[PDB]
Amino acid sequence: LGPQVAEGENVFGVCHIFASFNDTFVHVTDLSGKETICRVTGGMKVKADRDESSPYAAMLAAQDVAQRCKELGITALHIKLRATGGNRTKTPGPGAQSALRALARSGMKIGRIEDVTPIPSDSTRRKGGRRGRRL
Amino acid sequence: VVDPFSKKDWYDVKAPAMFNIRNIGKTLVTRTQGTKIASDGLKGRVFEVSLADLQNDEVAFRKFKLITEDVQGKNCLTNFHGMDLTRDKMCSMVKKWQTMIEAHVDVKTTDGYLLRLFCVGFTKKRNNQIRKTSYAQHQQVRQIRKKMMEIMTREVQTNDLKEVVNKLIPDSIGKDIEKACQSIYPLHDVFVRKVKMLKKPKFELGKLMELHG
Amino acid sequence: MRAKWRKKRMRRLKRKRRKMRQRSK
Amino acid sequence: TKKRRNNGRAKKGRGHVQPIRCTNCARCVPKDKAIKKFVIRNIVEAAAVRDISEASVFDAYVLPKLYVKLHYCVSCAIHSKVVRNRSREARKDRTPPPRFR
RNA sequence: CGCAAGACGGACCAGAGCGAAAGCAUUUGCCAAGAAUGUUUUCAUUAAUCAAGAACGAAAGUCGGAGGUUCGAAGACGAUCAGAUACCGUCGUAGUUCCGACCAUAAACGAUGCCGACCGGCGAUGCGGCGGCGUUAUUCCCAUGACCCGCCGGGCAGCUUCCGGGAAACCAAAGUCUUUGGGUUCCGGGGGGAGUAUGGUUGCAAAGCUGAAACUUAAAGGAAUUGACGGAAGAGCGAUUUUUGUACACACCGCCCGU
Ligand SMILES: [Mg+2]
Ligand SMILES: [Mg+2]
Ligand SMILES: [Mg+2]
Ligand SMILES: [Mg+2]
Ligand SMILES: [Mg+2]
Ligand SMILES: [Mg+2]
Ligand SMILES: [Mg+2]
Ligand SMILES: [Mg+2]
Ligand SMILES: [Mg+2]
Ligand SMILES: [Mg+2]
Ligand SMILES: [Mg+2]
Ligand SMILES: [Mg+2]
Ligand SMILES: [Mg+2]
Ligand SMILES: [Mg+2]
Ligand SMILES: [Mg+2]
Ligand SMILES: [Mg+2]
Ligand SMILES: [Mg+2]
Ligand SMILES: [Mg+2]
Ligand SMILES: [Mg+2]
Ligand SMILES: [Mg+2]
Ligand SMILES: [Mg+2]
Ligand SMILES: [Mg+2]
Ligand SMILES: [Mg+2]
Ligand SMILES: [Mg+2]
Ligand SMILES: [Mg+2]
Ligand SMILES: [Mg+2]
Ligand SMILES: [Mg+2]
Ligand SMILES: [Zn+2]
């Protein structure tokens, strides 16, 4: 079940890591990014709205997706790290580093890392008003 | 219930003959059930490949988009679709005490491919310079931009797509622009940073086979 | 009282007078 | 009582400056007044560096860096401690803090 | 992987530039305008400030058309709370965008009218001009661009000073003031009542301009000092001699606002 590839060569996929401040996505696709291998979100592991962005849920999701993609026959992954972007923050959430480290732990080979956060040349008005969020 | 990956098949994707390395990975597609043909879903896919994965001795911050054009029995045949730079290269090129000059042109090749080329350059600080900033006046910027546009135009419309990609692989256009603009104002980090495909000619199998050998 | 809101209250009272103190009356 | 000679902003010889939005709270603050910070860091942290360098398929593959421009309003800059209050004499000193060791 | 609409031009972007002020940042073209510098050109007092009278004038707002992506007064909900009619979150109407008519108000601020003269240093910076060893590009040559060292003239600013001012904070102007007179416009007279009533005038409206009195009160207010608090980290006129803010000083168990 998978590609017929010699032991020396590595089958490559692309891992999209969406690290928000509310959730974390680890998504695996082929090199064209049109076919999905496995997608696991941080909300599937923890049954609480607080811990969806926690490093622990990201680590669990990374291990689950690594096992699923190792079943099918993908041994190496390219990494596309993404933040929410747009009008909002460009800084990745707290689960990105933990998810990446867990993905490395599970025996997966690591290709090239690339930041793919969407950056406007200029955008629509941001939510909040003149005085901002006063909490 | 029923595994969707039991009906999947793996195909091998090839790069055009312009590059040294040909096998650029594998891809997956659902088998034909008579409703949807696997070939139709296979076509039209875009792959972003770093230049270091296509040529051994070339830089890795230049990426190429290749689009599958035909399927030949477990062999997807791709063609040039675009070129771009990595995010960190562009982010590290832009600095605070210098001038940035950008230009874009729309040029058609001899074989019908219409391209949009983008070029970027930065002013260079002198070796013995004591002044903190290195700013070019507006007329100097306009002259530099016009020199960029004419050089980018004269290196595409004369050649065809196969020769255009050959010039893009080492980025000789950027070196020509950098050399030509020394007299106006010294420039470093001159690059052709993005290339877009606007219009394609009608698909020809013989052209693709000549492109792949 | 903040001077801005005092001014707004004065304006609203004047508008109320103007509605009551009609020119027709 | 004027607290600063430059009024806490960098506006000289012009009338209006377009506002930007605070990264923290999305408040509108003039660009010259805002507190700016350029952050260049590594995508992977210190432990992740050693964990990734062994699992990579390349030899001496350099990890990419993250470049971010951050804008803060006065309240968010003070609350986040990126900026602190100084003495009346020490306010004038506008040398950046000695981060270079 | 494409398509469509609308709005905005990130990074470069600075105590940098332009504009009478509001204000002004993707490329290219067209149109008219302008400061500064250069000048052994021309006119020869043609000038400065300005009742009356005019042009422009952020945002919001009003009336007609066109579009309506995002955001979003009002509003409907969910939370928080002793209570929230608020702060927080989900939606969301006018509006936010363009054209044509109104409106003329901002902490429209340098809280500092314009023209002219004089009165200390220093290093940068933007524009124009002048001079000069030396590095670079235009394959050679001048010459022109990029650096380097200076000089002059306008411009945005900075540091320093027992120039002198000022209650001080501070100011090379806020100096050249009892040693009081260069020209000229606007404008203030203890704190409230009050920018309120009325009259006039402008506007479709909202409102804009001009603008009192009766009455009430012994202080209100500026700068700085020592304390006390905080759900913050020889020198000065003189009091006086961890940082910081204060409207507290019977010192937060304070003071104080409106029903
Ligand atoms: Mg959450
Ligand atoms: Mg959730
Ligand atoms: Mg707060
Ligand atoms: Mg203003
Ligand atoms: Mg500041
Ligand atoms: Mg000016
Ligand atoms: Mg831009
Ligand atoms: Mg008048
Ligand atoms: Mg308006
Ligand atoms: Mg409006
Ligand atoms: Mg309308
Ligand atoms: Mg709300
Ligand atoms: Mg909303
Ligand atoms: Mg006024
Ligand atoms: Mg101001
Ligand atoms: Mg005033
Ligand atoms: Mg000068
Ligand atoms: Mg200039
Ligand atoms: Mg010069
Ligand atoms: Mg006098
Ligand atoms: Mg009085
Ligand atoms: Mg009285
Ligand atoms: Mg003594
Ligand atoms: Mg004494
Ligand atoms: Mg305070
Ligand atoms: Mg104060
Ligand atoms: Mg005190
Ligand atoms: Zn903020």
Image (spheres, coloured by chain):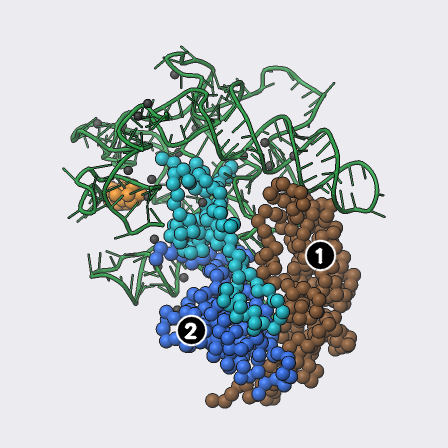
Chain colours: A blue, B brown, C orange, D cyan, E green
Please state the horizontal and vertical placement of residue A9, each as a whole percent of the image. 64, 79
- For the question of whether residue B81 can be seen, the reply is no
> Which x, y percent locates residue E110?
43, 35
What residue is shown at x 62% (from left), y 48% (from top)? B99
Residue depicted at x 50% and y 89%: B2
| Numbered mark located on residue B174 in the image | 1
Residues at discs 1 and 2 both on one chain: no
Q: Quick one: A85 or D58, which is closer to the camera?
A: D58
Inspect the image, locate mark 1, and give the three-letter code of the amino acid beneath it: Gly
Mark 2 belongs to chain:
A
Is residue B58 at all visible to an observer of this figure?
yes
- Cα separation between marks 1 and 2: 46 Å
Q: Which mark is residue B97?
A: none
Image position of B12 (left or right of A99) = right
Mark 2 — residue? Answer: A57
Image quadrant of residue E234?
A: top left
